[PDB]
Image 1: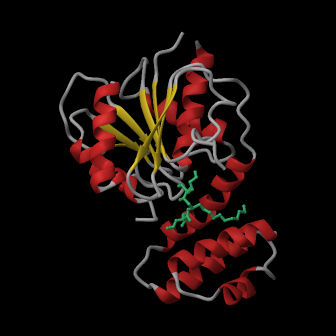
Image 2: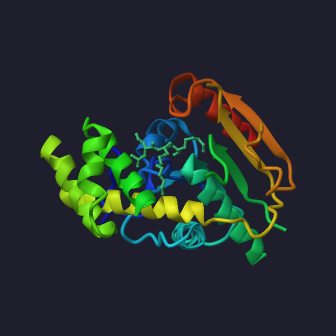
Length: 253
Ligand SMILES: *C(=O)[C@@H](CCCCCC)[C@@H](O)C[C@H](CCCCCCCCCCC)OC(=O)[C@H](CC(C)C)NC=O
């Protein structure tokens, strides 16, 4: 679930709704999968797609990822306006996709940010090291002893996969390897991302209960509506948070 098939499809149907209504396109969080969206997708009365981060995705920058996701999206719906959402890391990518579409043009795209905005050797190790800790129970200092002395990113990814496998032999090595590696690149991409223009279109922030607009005022002119959703950073897309999100999506559209 914190893993994606690195040879899987980038664009995927999260529901099978058959309708002439414009699809909702949903951008993965940092983990890269669309698993988080399953409940939302199963409850929407609109065709919904998920974008997952695979080996095809250019993770050199948010710019390149956004342009690639736009490319995928066009194979389903050639022309905008588009209905795009992003959850947490995905909010930043969704923003850049809409910024790029705006630049390509008076645009009427719909943008929903689910608890995220244009956020966020040693940094390399702390990234892979944090990665290992999410897959194992291994104490911080023992992971850091295996990784810090190593001499590049690829040596650390390989050691990370080894350490995770020792704890969980049934995880695919190719998936673990892609996930460790891409995680570093996703962080790097984010760290180097700088919106180059104010977004004019309308943005809706849906931030979890547990500034107010996540600094969307410095990057966007148009009606930034902020709704607060019951739950924490994870649970706003399940249960009571979810049901309220669907209602807000259903009336905005
Ligand atoms: C959204 O997806 C984020 C953001 C949460 C806060 C909302 C503000 C937008 C969420 O997944 C949190 C987290 C971010 C990773 C932080 C650790 C970075 C390490 C610092 C080193 C940087 C040096 C380059 O995601 C996670 O904690 C885990 C994701 C990975 C892929 C396992 N989730 C674990 O369950």
